[PDB]
Length: 313
Length: 312
Image (cartoon, rainbow over all chains, first blue to last red; front, side):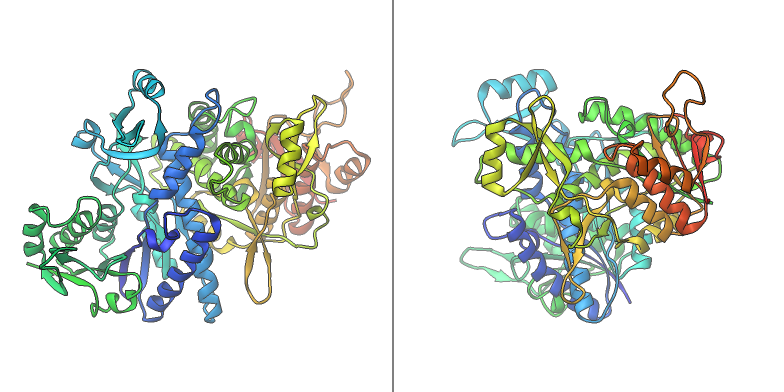
């Protein structure tokens, strides 16, 4: 009855090509739920997290497609929306699967906020694109009016970029822990969580930014005193010389060794880098192993028999 | 004591369906301050709310994209409003409780409600949802999606969807568990995400909305709550609009309200459902139900304001 925080990736929620159509997602989630059911069968208790890239982007585009006079919801509200959207899909599918196996349990979806620091370098150097392509005139206006920041897209137009600060604490950790005590499967920290900052006087205030789901999941695992941090992606694990000549997939590696590779740019900042950073952080802060593997091989990954096991030292 | 408190539109958005974050944050702060007073007074609570303006806004946005872009189903939009409105309520309530000395977290429960596919409403939809469309746009949407529309006095067209009666709250147990851990729980947003039972145990989401008051009354009965509270804009139920007499009923036997209801005194688009919900709670549990104003919530919870419905 050990506890594992399992961080799902895009392949568990959306179809090939980033399709957020209800059809595509329901099929992907069915596959992911079946596999998660296997893991629960092996005796694990879990807190399942997930990303929300295509989904939050879709919502951003939708609100921006409205007539100029209509209000656009802020990014943190869009993020909250994705927690219910993706969360419900996983919740409904997993419950159905467990039921089909004779297990009658309800899967809660915890609306989750993540505390970030206002001093984080990302707030002054936003680089995460979110939403549709903006025209020059509209973008310059948004910058003048709301202080939005943009990056030029080589194919034409501009992309709004927002901060991606590092997670400091999981505000709703206690609700997640309580949910876990009551159910073997809990969905939380969707999209990396809703970012808030502490204002003077103890007041928490939501901010327009995104938080890396892997870094956040690692922090959650540490704060829950989880027995294991699992990152499920679309590759067998971590590899050095990935997609290159001397490519080699690691089966086990000391966090200290991976940290060296990380500092040399061996892991793309847009994919495996954050996952390796997350795994290392978990090992350093808890002293317990973390594993990065394929969603397909999840059952074995959890047993540490597949994927890359990041070890202490 | 456990009270199920059904919040209305004035608690979440601004007049004229103003769903901007500024207007909703302000509205929610006002409602949360009042709810915090209720909790400080000793009550434990499951707080529900509607989502009319919010779910309508989502539909409007999804349809604003080029026709080929994926459109999310109504059940997903409803779920989205639960996190949207839920987050706002949760955030502000926690802040208000903290200032009053209660350092607690407020959970938001994603909630589904079971309905029956044979419900008469499915083939005779009458619940208006979404933005107001023009005649040409509407007929085009009917050909494109098979949607049904209702024309208003001003010539505007609004989509109408089924609003079947709630049968059971699928996530009742999660709501009960949350309530055991926290004095304030937000659940059943918008009346709940509707689903129907199919071959086996399978639950199938359906295109429809459920009345939030009827669903709240059902939840209150299934949680064995001590009180069902419906907070709205009016001080209570009105049956007399003449210069003389009491303005709003202070208390009334279930059978008395039922008679007024059967006479047409309460429009199905407004007070009708609230009265039906209060009557149902009283008949099923024998405990009192009250319909009052959000402003006077503190007196309402105590049954010293609003219309108190009693068994009889």
